[PDB]
Amino acid sequence: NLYQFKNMIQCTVPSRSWQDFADYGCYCGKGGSGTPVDDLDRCCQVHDNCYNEAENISGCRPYFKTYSYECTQGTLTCKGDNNACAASVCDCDRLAAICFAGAPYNDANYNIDLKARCN
Ligand SMILES: [Ca+2]
Image 1 (cartoon, rainbow, N blue to C red):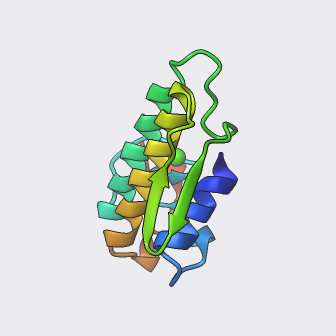
Image 2 (image 1 turned 90 degrees about the vertical axis):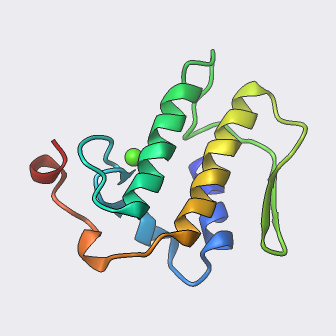
């Protein structure tokens, strides 16, 4: 769920406030369309697409599904007790969190005008 994803981000990128990734480019947060503006945005595009794919699973609601995971000593792990939905969503979140940690953060790309720039 989003709370868990927030925690994944807090654990792979403790140097930023989680909310720095909640409204960035065309895909991080709200958004879900247009040209990814940079590598961080591309991380979010893959994440968004990953969620859309997980939503094909019956009863699978990525913002809400509580999965089983651990963030310890620099590593994120999706646990074996996860059903197909939980495993898929956890993987989406894990990969995105790792992606965020390796992407440059451009302040100019925070809170961009989606209606104008993400068509
Ligand atoms: Ca999004």
